[PDB]
Amino acid sequence: GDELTRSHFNALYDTLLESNLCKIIEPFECVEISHISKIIGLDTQQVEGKLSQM
Amino acid sequence: RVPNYEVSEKAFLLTQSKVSIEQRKEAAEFVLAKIKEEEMAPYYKYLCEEYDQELYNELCKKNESKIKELNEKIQKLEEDDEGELEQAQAWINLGEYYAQIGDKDNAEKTLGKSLSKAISTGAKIDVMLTIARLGFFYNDQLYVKEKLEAVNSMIEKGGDWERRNRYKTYYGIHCLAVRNFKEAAKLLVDSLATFTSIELTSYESIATYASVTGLFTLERTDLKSKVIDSPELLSLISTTAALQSISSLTISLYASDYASYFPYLLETYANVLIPCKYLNRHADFFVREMRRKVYAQLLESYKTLSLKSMASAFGVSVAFLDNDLGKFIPNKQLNCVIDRVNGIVETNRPDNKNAQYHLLVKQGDGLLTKLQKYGAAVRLT
Amino acid sequence: TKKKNEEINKKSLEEDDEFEDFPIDTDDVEVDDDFTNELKAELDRYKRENQ
Image 1 (tube, rainbow over the protein chains, first blue to last red):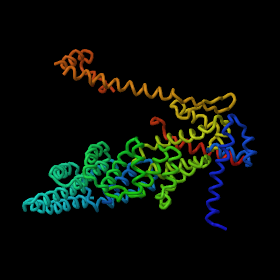
Image 2 (cartoon, rainbow over the protein chains, first blue to last red):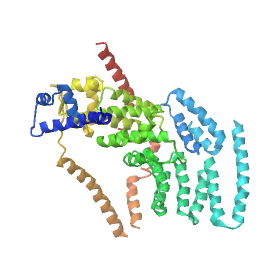
Image 3 (spheres, one colour):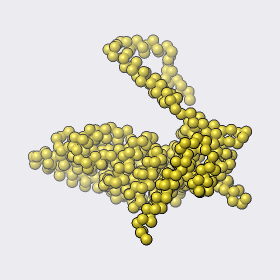
Image 4 (cartoon, helix red, strand yellow):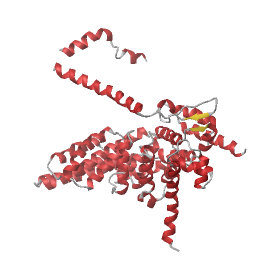
């Protein structure tokens, strides 16, 4: 209903996507990628590409 | 104004045998046009070696007309008595008539008087600018350097922001010609925004140059900010093939797409590097740098890859990848070892205090050396 | 005269003209690698595709 809010919410998706991942792997070292994948709730391969970018 | 730079750009094409026959002869027409029109006969002589009697008559005429004209004009401008205004102007004009026909020698003498004889600091800078352009013309770089070293002294003396800009853009081109790209980039990005062209190349040329350097030197984060999100580039889109190719390469480098990176590598070579005069000589050097850089980029994020994965990604065979990695490994930039028995690509990263220790000793040997010799000299004397 | 001493002593190793005897007698290396690569990338592609 708010065209301005909607636009800025795709962006929000993306900067928050980061926020969730960082928190999960912060205590661990040598964490399985399968473990990450379940929590975030996004497919195995998709995650590899994001992480490599980060 | 337009021929002063443009002639050299076309002429360069002609020289080269790299260029396609279609392009070579497209340029040939362009050159011949401007000879007759600007009456370049002295200089034309220089270029012909590197490449009708009516032309010659055109010289002989135009010369004696232009000579007789200016002669008595100048003679009268000196006679009637005030030097601040008339004598100074008259020498400017004299240099300009030499610069049109490209006699270097007689211009050094005339524009030299103008500098010596007291005038506004503005006035000094402006005049020097022409001498530097003739150096760039001649395709001698060291001639440009001596002049522009003086120009730089006067820049903060005068304090015009107008000429700080113009100075930046000349020095920008000089540096594009030498290997050193680091200084070129800094100057080059600012000048996308600002520079009314003066006796130097069009803004389309200047645009492709900022994109090219940006790849080479810039850190990743900073390529994105300054270049992709450039207000200038985005509005300018692509109205040229050269600008299009370089843009396509930038988008895959940042996006970590690798399949399309290699088609794109090939494209920029054809449509950017060879047309551009200054970057032609660095054609080999650039593609080397870029190929190290991409391989590097991917290896930074992976502790390991398998050979099949990496090769399919870039789009080359596994055999083609292996021969190429091993070029760049002893020169140290990719920082990776390769197992053959298990097919694996390990990536060692041992850079730490060790890296920095080697840089300091090597450069150190050199400071010691210089010092010893200057010491000995003076002691004798 | 310190300088003059240098040049004279040196001369016997230089003899007649160790300067002009020799000429009277007689990434920058690597070739155009674009071409090699062009062809490699298409030769890979072909097989990839028809497989």
